[PDB]
Each structure stands twice: as structure tokens, then as C-alpha cells.
Image (cartoon, rainbow, N blue to C red; front, side, top):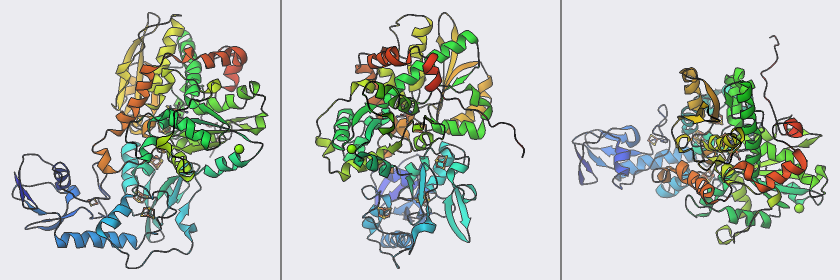
Length: 579
Ligand code: 402
Ligand code: SF4
Ligand code: SF4
Ligand code: SF4
Ligand code: SF4
Ligand code: FES
Ligand SMILES: [Mg+2]
């Protein structure tokens, strides 16, 4: 093929779109609705408009290159068309970037600036109440910002295959939302927030908990605990122009103290707790044979997927609470026993890469004696904004350490945020528990990686067992619908709703398509976690000295006694009722 782009001749045999061929040859072409190798097929934004000689204006994002094509990407006719489309989008967009939560990284704003587009009539709604949906515990919608680009809809389909995010006809007008415009929580939605990640603007956001936190911080009698998820220390640095894959663990501990938090702990400690219970439970299920398989229960997105699509598997879920919930349980019980604080005055806050974590924390039964396990959950984005609002020079901060009591963690807990992380961490303890030894080789590389469905055969106590790691909610459906579950007897299965693991969560920092092309965001973030595991002395959850002291002095033996009573949570399919 011979391609002419802006007077430059190209000789290629590649079969691809004009947009991507231009991107591969450093030729600038704008784009909006195009994401994850798909565009808005029904109402194309036409921001990727280029001029093909002999044909006219075409959309470069979905037009294959052909031999003899003469393309102009920066002609006048092209730029006026693109400027016209952006202007029309501004006519339905509340253009007030000042208080907006996408101010520092909004794809639309940089398109408005690039083409210097102005609205024919400034969209200024008198009352955003009808445009805004804040009924969910995880998601919020602001349709004053929605461009109707369909990226959220496509993302939902690709990532979860639930199609919970739909195009809707709201009284003659086209909008996006849940089925029948219901609250997302009341539908088959997983609350994974992958639709947020795909949104170029502030139309989709997480359900804010920042008022919960700030009100608790300012309350004199409240002792506010904060504990961040594995993925946060590998991600939040992106929002401070520090690049990708930068371990900023120490900076976060310091920033949290300057924010006024009363105690700095870590969810990775709770991750070690989850492994303690789960690995013990796995050994229990082996000696009992059943119920197999055992599924992980730490991902609330997967829990909702099970509840909404596979309720017969609810009993097969691990009884062990998620690292977030199992931490919060101990924060209201164990922590006061070693501090003297009044449990009612304890306020536990977590920092999560996940929007579904907010729903899990607000589950009615996720409490004890009137005390919530987790009082508030803020996303990686929310913490970052909280830091910038306090004008904390994050990139200039010294590394400080967390408080050890519930802040120490092994390398096993560190890799939780990556796909296959929980599986590998659980095997490190389950093997040592069953064989009653301290095994040297603990690296399970075969369950790592970005493959959708990963299986492995493991040898536990002179017996072989089949494990599986499900990477992404869509791959759960594939694993079940295709009958892969029945090819062999699986004993232990990890499931994560977000592909790549929690590092690709819905509460994670946004990454513009032009950095996604150059950076493998899922591997680069996960690398930080794996590097920590490699450099740590303790790489097994049961070697967590702070955790061992907690169990020895308070809980006793894992999987039984008081631990089984308050650190566990079982999901049950609804009792029979009719209708
Ligand atoms: N609870 C919990 Fe988890 C832990 O530890 C986080 O905290 Fe995850 C992360 N990062 C999230 O959100 S949840 C699913 N298990 C894998 S990692
Ligand atoms: S979504 Fe983007 S363009 Fe719209 S107001 Fe917010 S920052 Fe500005
Ligand atoms: S909510 Fe966001 S991703 Fe979905 S159509 Fe609107 S602007 Fe596009
Ligand atoms: S939270 Fe997940 S399941 Fe729900 S609409 Fe968004 S992408 Fe779909
Ligand atoms: S994989 Fe992690 S971030 Fe994604 S829904 Fe599950 S718990 Fe939340
Ligand atoms: S980016 Fe090509 S039509 Fe929208
Ligand atoms: Mg205070």
C-alpha cells in the first residue's frame, strides 16, 4: 500500500485504521469517543475527522487505510468540522472547570483548548437535581457533563459483559444510566467503576465519602484510623506528575499524618489476616473434602456478580472477610484492647482503588455491637484531592513509616492488588499449614500475568490440587458459561472483577488514551507490589510479627474460636419466597 498523509508518502502493508497508523507514525489526530479499540457506532463524535482525497471527510478511528489514499489531517475543512462538533458538545455541557473534579485531567477541556471551540449558547442548567443521580453507594452521575460518547457503555460490556450501563430514552432525550433508570445498586451492576475509568469527563464519579472523613477528623472525640489498600501506594503518584510505577508508600504515610489522621495503619495487614483465615479454611476444606471449589470473597464486585448471576456459588465463597472488612472488625475490637480507646470513638477510614469497596463497607451486617467495621471509604482519587486541597507538597515529602500494631505486612499481603496475588499469597500459607513446614520456594509465577483465565496444578502435602485465577468479571462469565469449570475439579479459585487486579480498580487515577498506548498501566502498577514482596524479609502472611502477636494475645487460633466468630462473613442465597 502507498499512503499519502499531509504530503508525506508511506509504504506499508499493515491493515489498520487511519488513526492508529497515524499514531504509529507520530501524526497528530484527535479522538474522543474512541477507546478500547471501539467508538460510538451510533452517534460518532467525529473528532477524529480527517480528509481523504476523492472521498471527503471520514472518521479516522474506524476507517481502514487503503492503497492510493491521500489524507489531510490538518486542512481547514477538517478543523472547522472538529471545531463544530466540540462546539455542539459545549451546548449540552456545563462548562465550569473551576470546582470540577476532572479539572486537572479532562480530555474534553484539552479538546476545547486545542481547537479554541466556543459554545453557541453556554449550557447553564438552573437546577442540576434532575441531571444528577447520587442514589448509589459507589457511583454518581452528573449528566450536565455527559458527552454521550458511549465509552462507559462499551467499557462495561468489555470489562464485565453485564451491560449494566445502558443508553436510555428519558422522555424523548438520550441519556446513560442503569436499567430502567434505577439506582445502580438495585440492578445487576457490579459497582466496579470501570465505566468511570473510561469516562473522559466528570459525568461519572465515585460516591464521595470525603465529608465523612473530614467531619470525623474535625470531631474532637473521634480517633480516626486510616489504612490504604495495596494498589494505592503504586498508583497515587500518577496524580502528582511523578510518572508511572513509582513506589510512594513512605510519602503516603507522611501525607496522611499531615492530613491529621490519628493513626496510620495498612490494609495489607488485613490482607495478611484474610490469608490467615482463608488458608486455614482451605486446609479445613481439604481434610473435609468440600465444599469445592472455594472462591475468594475479598472482591465486592465479584461478590455482587455471584449474588446477581450465580447465587448457587455463594455458599462456596470463603467465609473470611475481605482485608478491608476484616481489618475494620479488628480496628473496633483488637485495637481498643491495646490502646485504651473507646470503641465507639474509633473511626476507621480506608483508601481504596475500588468504588465497590464503598458498597461493601456500607453493608448492613458489616458491623458489630452497633459499630461499623469500616466507617468511610475514599478512593485513590479522593485521597489525592484531599492532599492537594491541604496544599501538601507530596512529591517533596520524606518517607515515614506506619504504626506497627496493624501496619506491618508481609510480601504476601503486598501483592494482593495484582491479579493472582491473593492466590499466590494464600498458597504460601496453605502449603506451610498443611505440610507443617517452612517452605523455601514460594513464588507461583504461573498464576501471575494479564491472562484472562489462569490455571495451575499445585502439590499440597503429597497431593495435587487444581487452582484457577479469574482475571476480570467478563472472564468469570466466560469461565462459567463455557463450562470450563467442569473440565476438572477445582479446589480453590481467585476472582477479581477488574482486569489486572485492584491496580486497575474503578477508584484509580484516570489515564488518558495517549498514555495507555505507551504504558501497560496494569503491569507497571503491579510491578511495584511484586517488587515490595521481593525486597521484604517476611514473605508469608503468618510470618507477620504484629499479626502473630494479635492472634496470640487476642484472637487465638485462626479459623476457629473467636476468630471464626467475628472475622468471618458468609453470603447466603435468598430464602425461598414467592413471588
Ligand atoms: N479489601 C481488600 Fe484487597 C486488599 O488487601 C484491596 O484492598 Fe483490593 C486492592 N488494592 C481493593 O479495593 S480487594 C480484592 N482483593 C485484592 S486487593
Ligand atoms: S468535565 Fe472537563 S471540561 Fe467539563 S467542566 Fe469538568 S473539567 Fe471542565
Ligand atoms: S458518562 Fe462519560 S463515558 Fe459515559 S457517555 Fe457520558 S461522557 Fe461518555
Ligand atoms: S460499575 Fe461496572 S458493572 Fe456497573 S455500570 Fe460501571 S462498568 Fe458496568
Ligand atoms: S478487583 Fe479490586 S478494585 Fe476491582 S472491584 Fe474487585 S475489589 Fe474493587
Ligand atoms: S473518535 Fe472517531 S468517531 Fe469518535
Ligand atoms: Mg481530629
